[PDB]
Amino acid sequence: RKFFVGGNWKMNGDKKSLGELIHTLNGAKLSADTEVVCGAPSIYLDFARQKLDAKIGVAAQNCYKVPKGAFTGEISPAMIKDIGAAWVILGHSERRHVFGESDELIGQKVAHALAEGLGVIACIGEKLDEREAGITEKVVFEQTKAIADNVKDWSKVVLAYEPVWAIGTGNSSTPQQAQEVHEKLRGWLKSHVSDAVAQSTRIIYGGSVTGGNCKELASQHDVDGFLVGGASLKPEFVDIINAKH
Amino acid sequence: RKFFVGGNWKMNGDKKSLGELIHTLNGAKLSADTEVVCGAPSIYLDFARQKLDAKIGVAAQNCYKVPKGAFTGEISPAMIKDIGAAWVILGHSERRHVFGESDELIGQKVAHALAEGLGVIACIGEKLDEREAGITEKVVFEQTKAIADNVKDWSKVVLAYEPVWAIGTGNSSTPQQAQEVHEKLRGWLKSHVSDAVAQSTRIIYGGSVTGGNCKELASQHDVDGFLVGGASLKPEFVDIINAKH
């Protein structure tokens, strides 16, 4: 399983600052066997794919579930590929919990994105109240199933476990905490899809990943890399790409 | 009051087909006294502004309510300006009724967009069940109020009345239905803002505007132009821009 690091830029940047960000990435010393993907704001996807080195992938931060139609403000996979990008992040915590995106809708987006030839970083995660009541597993299993029912081919899917309480808070999951969820998620894929899919599917951690904490998380058996928010806008994104070196 | 025609491309097009659409519009004989604005998908906003002639405006189809932050999938007015565009469509029917955007959220977006220096096309409109229950006035007044509460300066605001039952359905408002509402909306601006704002604010109609029905809609005293969806993608958008001549 190849180590995978996505950078979710979220709603940040302009052409100048993202140009500097990209320029630094392009000239940085990166471990050759990290698969790197940068999720840019939709308004800069075209710019980002033109400027970023071709061996670094580009992800839309969201999309809708048909190629075209009367959905003011939405973009489709067809548009994302037209721009040269090959990934989309779906089901991100902010889409679910600020913008009310349901499991059903996310599963539809996953099915469509994959049929259109995109790769998907599919995000799941529990809220603090769910963790404390002891349902972490039931919650991420329910979310993963709603994704898995819409995945016919896992080659181009990466699951992203991000506890909601870890996103942007400075409170990352402990290495042990992430490992136990990733292990359970991989056991879920083994039981519900196949053994081949469990052993080949990347499950990446996200939630306040930094240069200072990435090494210990990445040495965990079932953590396959990271989805990185805040630190993806910083030079230390490079150290996270190189978390195993 | 200057006649105003916006075209909302919605989730349609790629670089090739929009490049063709833009080329035709650029070359078309357009009435010089029509203010024209095209609402491009976010992924193509930069491309659209490069390609469209400067006398045609470019609108984002939606935006968020702060300049930056942890809002995966969103774009800000600062990003819209960075790309050279000066408008945004807010509170569109699809945002409200497909994507659950509330009056309070649209209001905060309106305040922020205007403070950042954008123009806003603020959309309102009742649903079929609301019209059929005799409640049209109450719904559009409530919607208009939530916009007005967040507008200090109306110079760069256009109000767009688009009853939801007319959007995309082929079932336009009649000239008389539309006039009855526009007239009430203008009277609302008169009583709750000022006479000056009532006589100077464009209130445009939208909902299945076509080449064949636009002239009779535009000659109504209080219809000041159009927000055009599906016909914005066709040659007849030219005829709608020329509705007064």
Image: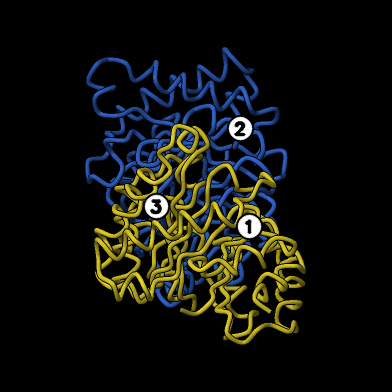
Chain colours: A yellow, B blue
> How many callouts does the rendering have?
3
Q: Earlier in the sequence, mark 2 or mark 3?
A: 2
| Image coords of residue A32 (percent x, y) | 62, 87
| Tag 2 and tag 3 share a subunit | yes
What is the distance, in whole Å, between disc 2 and disc 3 at their CAs? 32 Å
Where residue A115 sits, quadrant-wise, is: bottom left
**Residue drawn at (66%, 48%) of the image:** B69
**Residue drawn at (33%, 33%) of the image:** B163
Q: Label 2 belongs to which residue?
A: B108
Closer to the camera: disc 3 or disc 1? 1
- Disc assigned to residue B240: 3
The relative height of residue A146 versus residue B197 in the rendered view (above or below) is below
Q: Is residue B11 left or right of residue A215?
A: left
Q: Secondary structure at mark 3?
A: helix
**Residue drawn at (42%, 33%) of the image:** B161
Q: Nearer the viewer, residue B69 or A180?
A: A180
Q: Amino acid at mark 1?
A: Gly
Closer to the camera: disc 2 or disc 3? 2
Q: Label 1 belongs to which residue?
A: A229
- Disc assigned to residue B170: none
Q: Chain of mark 2?
A: B
